[PDB]
Amino acid sequence: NSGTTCSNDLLQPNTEVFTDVCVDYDLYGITGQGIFKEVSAVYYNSWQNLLYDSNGNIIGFKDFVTNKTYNIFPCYAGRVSAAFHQNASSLALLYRN
Amino acid sequence: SGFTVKPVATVHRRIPDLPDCDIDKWLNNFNVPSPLNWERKIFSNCNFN
Amino acid sequence: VTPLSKRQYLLKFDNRGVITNAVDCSSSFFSEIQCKTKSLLPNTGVYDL
Amino acid sequence: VIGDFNCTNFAINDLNTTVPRISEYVVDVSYGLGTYYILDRVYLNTTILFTGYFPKSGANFRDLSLKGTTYLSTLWYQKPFLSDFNNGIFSRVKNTKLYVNKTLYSEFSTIVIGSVFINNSYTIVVQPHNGVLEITACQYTMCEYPHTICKSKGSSRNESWHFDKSEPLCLFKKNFTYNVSTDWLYFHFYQERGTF
Ligand SMILES: *[C@@H]1O[C@H](CO)[C@@H](O[C@@H]2O[C@H](CO)[C@@H](O)[C@H](O)[C@H]2NC(C)=O)[C@H](O)[C@H]1NC(C)=O
Ligand SMILES: *[C@@H]1O[C@H](CO)[C@@H](O[C@@H]2O[C@H](CO)[C@@H](O)[C@H](O)[C@H]2NC(C)=O)[C@H](O)[C@H]1NC(C)=O
Ligand SMILES: *[C@@H]1O[C@H](CO)[C@@H](O)[C@H](O)[C@H]1NC(C)=O
Ligand SMILES: *[C@@H]1O[C@H](CO)[C@@H](O)[C@H](O)[C@H]1NC(C)=O
């Protein structure tokens, strides 16, 4: 129970990545949730793995296992408008935009 | 209230600090020693599966 | 060898990620103006240092 | 005095014929020289403000290169050569080019950072090997007389700065490469909140 010769067999397995679905990620020490995509980036270097924003957000990343660049997008999180009348029993729903 | 969808799985990525031990490469060597000259090897500061 | 210090630097990036300009924000008054306006060539005006 | 073990004692002298020289070059961060890339992120067509450990513009350098011929003095392992790592250092190294039968070889001095430099603590050591760097940062047992020899046109002494029969325990181990035909190299070292 003391040393540095540990095994990554049961610690955390790597299986695959998912596309077009809001999923959680714990990439390179930073966590978040969102939807990934697939782009053709050429601005990555040997030591660069993330593409960051100018305000403190993540724009994309690159998986070193298969050498392809992605693009992380935030998924929908919004509210709905509901119109209601006193004499009525149901509601009128409106999803804006 | 807002509509926040839940994630379906978890995706993690990390870069390993120490290299792999490569125990299988040493255990599959073609020069099999005799019990009279058994071989000994020390492994430390590496990762193995 | 030269020492280091916790300072603030204005970094300019190109369309590929290569750093092209860096401003110390503490060398002269023009550097402070540039880092206050968050631009390499500030606009015409009167500022308080 | 850096270590505590007695690794070797062949030629021990006591002379004071060295002094750090102040360089004539001035730090110019106009075009990027002196600044470092951020952690493994990418910025595109933006202008940012970063609060970090940087050198001061309009400053002078100091040399700490030591070279000898089988003779080592006790004053070489003390101040001002054994400087203090207050918050960080930025170093410029000259790529010494040698030729052995019309074959290019590159080698420069090595750096060792630590706290007490004993086996009970960690110690970072960076040294090149013919165009290949080596960063270990392991709990090495270094003696108070560390040195390093040249592989090309070797010296009388032998490279002996640590005495460890088995590899001690540590967290990091990795090799790096660089162009052997360059002339100047740059290095940045610092720490923050216990992270080096
Ligand atoms: C880098 O960013 C600048 C600033 O947004 C871009 O300059 C703009 O370019 C568009 C398209 O040509 C023009 O309509 C704007 O008027 C420009 N604004 C300014 C302030 O110049 C520039 O195109 C970007 N470069 C790249 C390669 O995308
Ligand atoms: C980093 O490079 C050094 C130098 O090439 C490697 O050290 C060599 O290791 C082999 C294998 O044990 C020895 O046969 C050589 O004698 C070593 N050379 C020197 C100069 O020490 C080291 O193994 C490399 N490390 C990694 C992780 O690749
Ligand atoms: C939404 O549904 C469409 C239709 O099946 C599908 O193509 C898309 O991937 C879905 N998006 C998410 C985030 O579930
Ligand atoms: C990804 O690129 C790096 C650097 O070019 C290379 O070392 C590595 O083998 C590549 N991996 C794959 C799966 O192509």
Image (cartoon, grey):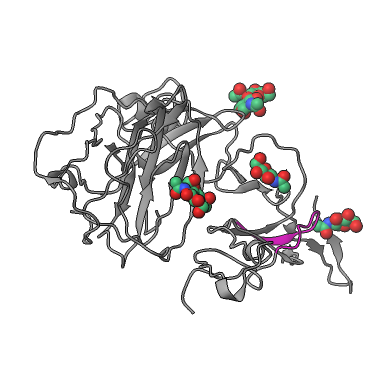
**Camera-side residue of C36 and D154:** D154
- The main secondary structure of the magenta stretch is loop
Residue D91, image x, y percentages: 33, 36
Q: Where A79 sits versus B39, above or below?
A: above
**Camera-side residue of A51 and D115:** D115
Q: Is residue A15 magenta?
A: yes
Q: Residue at x 19, y 49 (%)?
A: D10
**Camera-side residue of A38 and D13:** D13
- Tell me, yes or no, if residue D29 can be seen here: no
Q: Where D127 sits versus D104, above or below?
A: below
- In the drawing, does residue D24 fall left or right of residue D154? left
The picture quadrant where one finds residue D45 is: top right
Given the current orientation, which residue lies at the most extreme bottom position?
A1
- Tell me, yes or no, if residue D105 can be seen here: yes
Magenta range is A14-27
Q: Where A67 sits versus D180, above or below?
A: below
Q: Residue at x 62, y 48 (%)?
A: A58
Residue B18, image x, y percentages: 53, 59
Given the current orientation, which residue lies at the most extreme front position?
B36
Q: Where A64 sits versus D129, above or below?
A: below
Q: Is residue A61 magenta?
A: no
Numbered-mark total: 0
**Camera-side residue of A63 and C46:** A63
Given the current orientation, which residue lies at the most extreme top position?
C44
Residue D182, image x, y percentages: 46, 26
Q: Residue at x 51, y 68 (%)?
A: B42
- In the drawing, does residue D124 fall left or right of residue C21? left
Residue D50, image x, y percentages: 44, 41
Q: Residue at x 37, y 59 (%)?
A: D194
